[PDB]
Length: 129
Image (tube, rainbow, N blue to C red; front, side):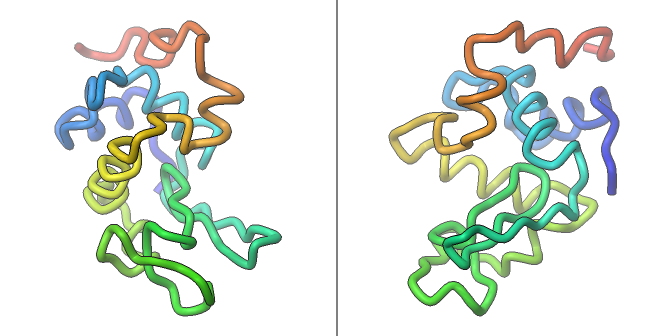
């Protein structure tokens, strides 16, 4: 599913991501912007031989289980593909664990890189709040 900007903020919010570990929807929406171009089915292979999944692009190195990342952990207790669903509960719930993992949104490289310190609210603009 390719989410809308505003119908992504929304799901995020009903899914408790809104100002989680102090990161506003703005952060989480921009983050999903650059990570998946708001598509729940974006998977991307690393040189790692790791693969990132879904919406917030969850790495298969420690966060989820797919079957072929020799080293990996499944710190979120879930099949990598459950991150690809139309419903964002898995990836949100995963998200929650990661951001909780010391380093904040920094765990998301395009977030550090493309959204960090930027007018992130711009992302939830006009959104029926």
